[PDB]
Image (cartoon, coloured by chain):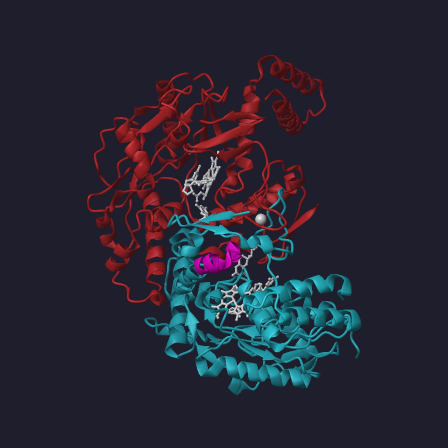
Chain colours: A cyan, B red
Amino acid sequence: RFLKVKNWETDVVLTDTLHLKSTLETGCTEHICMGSIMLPVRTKDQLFPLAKEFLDQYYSSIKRFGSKAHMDRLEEVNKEIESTSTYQLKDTELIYGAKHAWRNASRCVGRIQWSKLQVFDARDCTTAHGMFNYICNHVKYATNKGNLRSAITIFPQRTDGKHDFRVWNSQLIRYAGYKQPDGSTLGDPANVQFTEICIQQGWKAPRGRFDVLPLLLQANGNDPELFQIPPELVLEVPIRHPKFDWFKDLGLKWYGLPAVSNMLLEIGGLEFSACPFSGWYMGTEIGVRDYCDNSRYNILEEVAKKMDLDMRKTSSLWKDQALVEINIAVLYSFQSDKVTIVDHHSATESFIKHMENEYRCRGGCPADWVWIVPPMSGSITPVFHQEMLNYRLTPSFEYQPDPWNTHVWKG
Amino acid sequence: RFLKVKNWETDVVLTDTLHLKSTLETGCTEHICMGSIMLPTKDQLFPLAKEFLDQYYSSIKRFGSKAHMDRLEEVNKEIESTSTYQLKDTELIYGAKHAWRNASRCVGRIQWSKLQVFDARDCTTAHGMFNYICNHVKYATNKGNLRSAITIFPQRTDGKHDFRVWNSQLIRYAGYKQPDGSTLGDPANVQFTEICIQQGWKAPRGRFDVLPLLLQANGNDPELFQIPPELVLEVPIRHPKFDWFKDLGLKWYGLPAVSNMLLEIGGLEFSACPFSGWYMGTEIGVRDYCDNSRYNILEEVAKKMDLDMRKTSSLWKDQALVEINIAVLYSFQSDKVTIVDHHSATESFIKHMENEYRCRGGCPADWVWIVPPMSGSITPVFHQEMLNYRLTPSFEYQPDPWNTHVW
Ligand code: HEM
Ligand code: HEM
Ligand SMILES: Cc1cc(N)nc(CCCCCO[C@H]2CNC[C@H]2Cc2cc(C)cc(N)n2)c1
Ligand SMILES: Cc1cc(N)nc(CCCCCO[C@H]2CNC[C@H]2Cc2cc(C)cc(N)n2)c1
Ligand SMILES: C[C@H](O)[C@H](O)[C@H]1CNc2nc(N)[nH]c(=O)c2N1
Ligand SMILES: C[C@H](O)[C@H](O)[C@H]1CNc2nc(N)[nH]c(=O)c2N1
Ligand SMILES: [Zn+2]
C-alpha cells in the first residue's frame, strides 16, 4: 500500500511505502489520535525474529542479502541465542544500528546528518569509573573546541534486567536546580529532583544559578557513583546581544554540547540502556525552551523590563518581542565564540530536503510534526506546511523510566 | 479505555472518558499516526437520529421520559415514511452549538454556548440565500462588536438539490495571476476569482477586492451577488510605532466566516451553513500576511525596518513577524473591532478544557491546529497534551462545489 503526504506551501506530494516495515505501536487507534501525548528481560522466543529482521536489513544495506556471509551470520546468531539466550553484535552491526536509530528518530529535526556519527563502542566497560572515563572522552571528542562532532557512546547491553548500565543524568551536561524554603528556585527548575539525589549521594553543591551537575553513573546494576566532569572539558558560552549592551548583565550562559543520556537504544532485539549521544544545538532549544519556558529559567519578564516594552496587556506582544531578542542573542553568542549552532530556519529547510531525499531513496521518513515544528515562528518555517507520517522503525531510541524510580539499592 | 492528559507546565492531569462515545474514524492506526494530515439510507439514518435525540434529551434532564420516547417514536415513524426527518428548532439550536463544541481544531470554543442560530431552512432560491447571508453578516458584525452566528440552509435530500455557498469564506479578497507571472491580491483565491469572472463578475483587478458571493440553491447553477460594501467592515493596518507601516497599504476584514463546511446533526446533512466569530490576531498577521503562498509580505516589511537580511540567523523574518502582528492587533483595537491575541485565546482554551473535563469528561482537541503559528511554546496550549477524536454533531470539510457540480 501507498500513503501520500502533501506540502501545502509547494503542492509537492510524496508517497510513503516505508510505513509497511512498521512494527511498534503508535498509541493511536482509528478512534483516537495520541499524536500530542508525550509518552504514548526478553525471551529467546521473541528474540530470534527481531535478530533476523535486523540482520536481513543490515545485509541488504551492504548488498549481501542472501550471501553465504548473511546465512552464516544468521546461523551463528541463532545458535548463540539458543545457547546463551542472547547474542553479541559485530562492530559493523553496532555502527549501522546506532546510525539507523538516529535515522529512524521521528522527533529529530537534525536527521540530514544521520550518516556522520562517531560511534564509541564501550561494551568492554565494567565499572562506573570505567563509564566516567568513556564519557569524558566522548565529551572531549564531541566538543572538539567548539567545532562540534556528533557522537554516541554504547555501554554493555541489558542481560537479565538486574545488571543494567545506566547514566542517571538525563543529559551529560546540565545545570543544578535548588528549591528554596520560600518556594523560589535557583538555577534550572527542571533539574531540582536530580540535583537533590546528587546532594544526597554526597555532591558538594556550589548553589549558584549555573552549576554543571556531576555525572551519576551505574554499571552492571550496582548503585550509581558520582563524578565531576573536568571543568576544562565543559565548553560554555556567555550570552550577549549584538545591539543591547545590557543583555550581558543578565548573567546568562549556556553549555555548547547537547547530549541525551537517558534513552534506550534497541538494535536487533538487544537493549542498550546507557547510550549517551550528542550533536549540536538548534538555537531555539536554548532561547525558546530553556530560557523562556515558565517552568525553566523563565527570563521573559526581566528581558522585556530592560527593553522597556509595554507589559501591561498581553496584546502588546511583549513576550513575543522579548522572545525574538533572546534568540538573536543565543545565536549571536555561539557564532561569535565559534561554537556550532543552527538557527531554526536553516535546520527546518535542511530537514525538508533530507525528508524528500529519504522518500526517494528509502520510500519514507517517519516524522513527528508536533516535535519537528520549532517552538517559535512555527508557520514561517517550511516544516509547518509539511504533512508528515509518524510510525516506528527499529533500530530505535526509546524513552525509559528514570532509574531512581526502579533501582534496587545495594547500600 | 480511561485516558489521561498531562499538562507539562503545570503537572495538571485530566482523565478523558468522553472519547468512548467517539463515533467517526481518525485516519490513525496503531501503526501510523496521521495527526498532521489536513484531510485524513433509511437503515443508516435511524441509529444516527436516535444517538442524537438520546443526548439531546439527556442534556435537558429528560432522558427516558415519555416526551423523549414520544419523539424517538415520531422521528422513527417519519423516517420510515419519508426517508428523512425534520429537526425541531430546539434540536437544531442544540446541534449547531454542539457541532462547534465538538470542533477539535477550534481554539475559541470557550464561546460555544453563545451562538446565534439563524434557521434558514425555509429558503428556496439564491436571492433568498443572499438575503439571509447579508442579515447574518450585519448581525454578526454589529458595528465592530462581533457576535458569533450560524445560518443553516435546507438539509441534503437526494443529494441532487444541495444548497452550497461556493465561497470558502463569506468575505475574502480576489486573486489574479499576472502577465508579469506574479500574483495580484490573495493567491489562495485565484481559482475562485476566475470562476467568478467566468460566471460574469466584473472584477476591478485590485489587491483587496471583496469577492462576490456565489450561491447555489436547491442544486441549481450558482448566481453572483455583491455584499453591500457598507456591510463589509474592513480595518486599515497601521503600527503604533512605525509611521511608515500605513504606506504598505494593508487592510483586512473584521468578520471571519467559514462558509464551505458541512454540518451534520442526527444524521442530517446541512451542506450550506456559513458561520462566523471573531479573529485571533495571528490568523491575519502570521498566516494571511506572511505565508509564502499568501500575501507574503515579510521581505518588504523587513526592508522597511532595515534589518540584516543577509543571513537567516539574524532572525529578521522573526523580527518583522512580531511587528506585523502587533500592527494587526493595534489597528483592530483602535478601530474598536473585536480581535483576540494568541496569548489570551490559548489561555481561554486551557480554562475551557478544564471546564469540559470537569463537566463533560473530556474535550476533543487537535494540537496541530490549536497551537498558534507563532510563539507556540510561550502559550500554555503548547504544553498541554490533547486527545483528538470525532464527536457528532460535527462540522466536516467538503469538496469544493465546482468539482462536484454539473452545469
Ligand atoms: C547534529 C545536530 C542535531 C540537531 C540540530 C538536532 C536537533 C534536535 C531537536 C531540535 C530535537 C527536539 C529537542 C527538544 O525539543 O528537546 C531533537 C530530538 C531528538 N534527537 Fe536530534 N539533533 C541533532 C543530533 C542528534 C543525534 C546525534 C541523535 C542520536 C544519535 C539525535 C536523536 C534525537 C532523539 C532520539 C530525539 C528525541 C529526544 C526525546 O524524545 O527526548 N539527535 N534533535
Ligand atoms: C468566537 C471567536 C472564535 C475564535 C477566536 C475562533 C478561533 C479559531 C481558530 C484560531 C481556528 C483555526 C483556523 C485557522 O487557523 O485557519 C478555528 C478553526 C475552526 N473553528 Fe473556531 N473560532 C471562533 C468562532 C467559531 C465559531 C462560531 C465556529 C462554529 C460555529 C467555529 C468552528 C471552527 C471550525 C469548524 C474550525 C476548523 C475550520 C477548518 O477546519 O477549516 N469557530 N477557529
Ligand atoms: C543529540 C541532540 C541534539 C540536539 N540539538 N538536541 C538534543 C536535546 C534533546 C532533548 C533533551 C530535552 O528533552 C526534555 C525536555 N522535554 C522533554 C524531555 C525529553 C523527553 C521527555 C519525555 C517525557 C519523553 C521523551 N521522549 N523525551 C539532543
Ligand atoms: C468562525 C471562525 C473564527 C475564526 N477566528 N477563524 C475562522 C477561520 C478558519 C478557517 C479559514 C482558513 O482555513 C483555510 C486556510 N487553511 C486551511 C483552510 C481550511 C481548510 C482546508 C482544508 C484542506 C481542510 C480543512 N479542514 N480546512 C473561522
Ligand atoms: C504536550 C506536547 O506534546 C509537548 O508539550 C511537546 C510539544 N512539542 C515538543 N517539541 C519538541 N521539540 N520538544 C518538546 O519537548 C515538545 N513538547
Ligand atoms: C500540514 C499541517 O497539518 C498544516 O500545515 C496545518 C498545521 N497547523 C495548522 N493550524 C491552524 N490553526 N491552521 C492551519 O491551517 C494549519 N495548517
Ligand atoms: Zn494519530
Q: Is residue A43 visible?
A: no
- Residue range highlighted in magenta: A355-372
Q: Is residue B191 visible?
A: yes
**Vertical relation: B382 (above or below) B169:** below
Residue A107 shown in magenta:
no
The percent position of residue B121, horizontal first and vertical second, equals 47, 19
Asked if residue B242 lies left or right of residue B21, the reply is left
Which image quadrant: the C terminus of chain B?
Answer: top left
Q: Quadrant of residue A85?
A: bottom right
Q: Residue at x 70, y 19 (%)?
A: B69
The percent position of residue B364, horizontal first and vertical second, equals 58, 42
The percent position of residue A43, horizontal first and vertical second, equals 77, 64
Residue B120 or residue B406, whichever sits in front: B406
Asked if residue B286 lies left or right of residue A392, the reply is left
Q: Quadrant of residue B272?
A: top left
Residue B54 or residue A388, whichever sits in front: A388
Could you tell me what secondary structure mostly forms the magenta stretch?
helix
